[PDB]
Image (cartoon, rainbow, N blue to C red):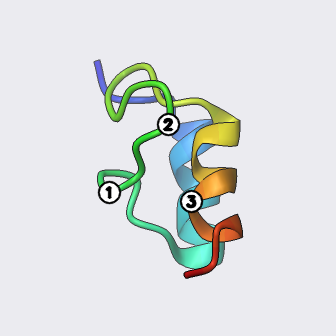
Amino acid sequence: VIAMPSVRKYAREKGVDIRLVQGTGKNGRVLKEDIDAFLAGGA
């Protein structure tokens, strides 16, 4: 039950490994704001 493609494509656009992302759930429960925060954090 991987996340929807509409969300994964975004990750690819900016370049972010969805797997590493850990918002609410790094699984079929990955949100759009999940990855948004990934990179936003910066470092």
Q: For the view shown, which residue lies furthest in the bottom direction? A: 43
Question: Could you say which is closer to the camera, residue 24 or residue 27?
Answer: 24
Q: Is residue 43 above or below residue 20?
A: below
Quadrant of the frame with the N terminus: top left
Q: Residue at x 70, y 39 (%)?
A: 33
CB within 8 Å, label 1 to label 3: yes
To which residue does mark 3 refer? 38
Residue 35: x and y in percent read 58, 51
Q: Residue at x 36, y 21 (%)?
A: 28
Q: Secondary structure at mark 2?
A: loop
Q: Choose the circle earlier in sequence order: 1 or 3.
A: 1
* Mark 3 surroundings: few (<14), some (14-19) or many (≥20) residues within 10 A: some
Quarter-of-image position of residue 2: top left
What's the amino acid at mark 2?
A: Gly
What's the amino acid at mark 3?
A: Phe
To which residue does mark 1 refer? 20
Left/right placement of residue 12 relative to residue 3 reads right
CB within 8 Å, label 3 to label 2: yes
Disc count in the image?
3
Question: Could you say which is closer to the camera, residue 27 or residue 40?
Answer: 40
Q: Secondary structure at mark 1?
A: loop
CB within 8 Å, label 1 to label 2: no
What's the amino acid at mark 1?
A: Leu
* Mark 2 surroundings: few (<14), some (14-19) or many (≥20) residues within 10 A: some
Q: For the view shown, which residue lies furthest in the front direction? A: 43
Q: Is residue 23 above or below residue 42?
A: above
Residue 13: x and y in percent read 64, 71
Q: Choose the circle earlier in sequence order: 3 or 2.
A: 2
Quarter-of-image position of residue 25: top left
Q: Is residue 20 above or below residue 26?
A: below
To which residue does mark 2 refer? 23
Q: Residue at x 55, y 81 (%)?
A: 43
